């Protein structure tokens, strides 16, 4: 693609510069180019990929929610609100499809270690979840089940291969809980997952260094925040 | 409000 | 251009939706399309044009300043920092050139009323100022003088045709003062302009309604902030 | 700091 002529190391360096400059669309394009070099990604590099696309799709989702709310109030005028909501929606779907394409070609199939495989399967669940937030057609149930299946495989691996305080295990459980609550209309499952994840992490904190303790308790607090919101 | 998914 | 098939009114409506969604690149593209319809812009429409491009170029300027600082520290490594600073710089220059092109074809020549003509000449000064912030070549002095000439014509009109509390007159004087301080290396001129503008506005406040008083004193406070910073 | 130009 457009980044084919740039060195992998230069793409990674520029992704870090783009993050410092809060230029997340550039950051995502640089990291897409780095993935397309065909080599596996390091821990740090996977984080850069995730940060970049999370910020891009995060702005699109926030805009879509603003426009969808205006559209709902309008249907309680002309086609413009629907048209512009559709424009933002299509761009969001394009970004999600791009990320899912990188995971499928070929990040997931080459990811053998628990840390990388769970990371990418969590990403796959997340981006199918973002597709599910805007879905309304014949394939909406299949989109939801694609999110569920990816989260579920990641959960099964993380429970077998990682300690309960592992940050990627915690962040996966957090997001699968949000999937249950917001997408699958399963609030009891969401609450049960968040509580069991929190409690089993709490019991494993004694094994950690001060720095690992900080990392794990930060994500546990997000689980606690959702539990307080939901109960 | 909307719930927290993982965020930095 | 790309917005040629959309109704003017629909472009304006979507520009307002894009502002609500904080989608300022979309907002700018919609307002560029509205300008290219060839009709003059209303007060409200001029504001939408200004807001859109100010937010777009504002993000570019902030990113350029981050990258320029990294680049300076690096020259006290490879080409990547310079390359990426140049990329952002070129995109910023492209946005400034687009705005200046709209002013020149043909917003300024059709603007007969003081309010519109001063607004567009202030915009021309602002975007030449943004070009000046990144300029280093043979034409840098001409870029600076282009900013000065536009601000100066706007000042001459505003002093003849508008009261000293008029918000566009105040905002023009504020930005011309910043031009003096930051671009023309004329801090004494910057300070004198900000003080004289503030004092003459203060003496005209007694003529205003409560709402106009609020509008004028808000911009006077920005003049005061700069004076406190500079003295 | 950098000075204030007009802003909403
Ligand atoms: Ca219950
Ligand atoms: Ca002096
Ligand atoms: Cl649209
Ligand atoms: Cl570059
Ligand atoms: Mg190579
Ligand atoms: Mg028409």
Image (spheres, coloured by chain):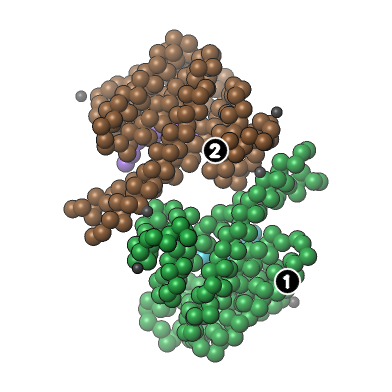
Chain colours: A brown, B purple, C green, D cyan
Residue at which label 1 appears: C142
Rendered view: A13 above or below A151: below
Residue at which label 2 appears: A28
Residue A212's quadrant in the figure? top right
- Determine the residue positioned at 39% across, 21% down: A150
- Determine the residue positioned at 63% across, 80% down: C152
Rendered view: A75 above or below C158: above
Q: Describe residue A147's horizontal placement relative to residue C36 as left or right.
A: left
- For ligand 2, which image quadrant applies? bottom right
**Crowding near pointer 1: few (<14 within 10 Å), some, many (20+)?**
few
Rendering coords of residue C15 (x, y %): 40, 60
Residue A119 visible in the displayed image: no
**Tag 2, which secondary structure?**
helix
Depth order, front residue of C192/B7: B7
Depth order, front residue of C185/A29: A29
- What chain does badge 2 belong to? A
- Determine the residue positioned at 38% across, 43% down: A90
Residue C183's quadrant in the figure? bottom right
Residue C53 visible in the displayed image: yes
Depth order, front residue of C117/C183: C117
Rendering coords of residue C116 (x, y %): 48, 79
Rendering coords of residue C115 (x, y %): 47, 81
Q: Residue furthest bottom?
A: C160
**Tag 1, which secondary structure?**
helix
Rendering coords of residue C16 (x, y %): 38, 61
Q: Describe residue A34's horizontal placement relative to residue A167 as left or right.
A: right
Label 1 CB sits under 8 Å from any ligand 4 atom: no
- What chain does badge 1 belong to? C
Depth order, front residue of C69/A166: C69
- Determine the residue positioned at 53% across, 13% down: A112
């Amino acid at each position: 693609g457009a980044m084919g002529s740039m060195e992998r190391a230069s793409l990674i360096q520029k992704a870090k510069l783009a993050e410092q400059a809060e230029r997340y669309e550039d950051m995502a394009a640089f990291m897409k180019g780095a993935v397309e070099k065909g080599e596996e990604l390091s821990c740090e590099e996977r984080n850069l990929l995730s940060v970049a696309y999370k910020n891009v799709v995060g702005g699109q989702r926030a805009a879509w929610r603003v426009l969808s709310s205006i559209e709902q109030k309008s249907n309680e005028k002309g086609p413009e609100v629907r048209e512009y909501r559709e424009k933002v929606e299509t761009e969001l779907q394009g970004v999600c499809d791009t990320v899912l394409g990188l995971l499928d070609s070929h990040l997931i199939k080459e990811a053998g270690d628990a840390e990388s495989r769970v990371f990418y399967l969590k990403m796959k669940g997340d981006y199918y979840r973002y597709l599910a937030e805007v879905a309304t057609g014949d394939d909406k149930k299949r989109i939801i089940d694609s999110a569920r299946s990816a989260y579920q495989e990641a959960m099964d691996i993380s429970k077998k291969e990682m300690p309960p305080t592992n940050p990627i295990r915690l962040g996966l459980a957090l997001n699968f809980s949000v999937f249950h609550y917001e997408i699958a209309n399963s609030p009891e499952e969401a609450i049960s997952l968040a509580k069991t994840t929190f409690d089993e992490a709490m019991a494993d904190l004694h094994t950690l260094s001060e720095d690992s303790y900080k990392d794990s308790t930060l994500i546990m607090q997000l689980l606690r925040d959702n539990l307080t919101l939901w109960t | 409000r909307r719930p927290s998914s993982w965020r930095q």
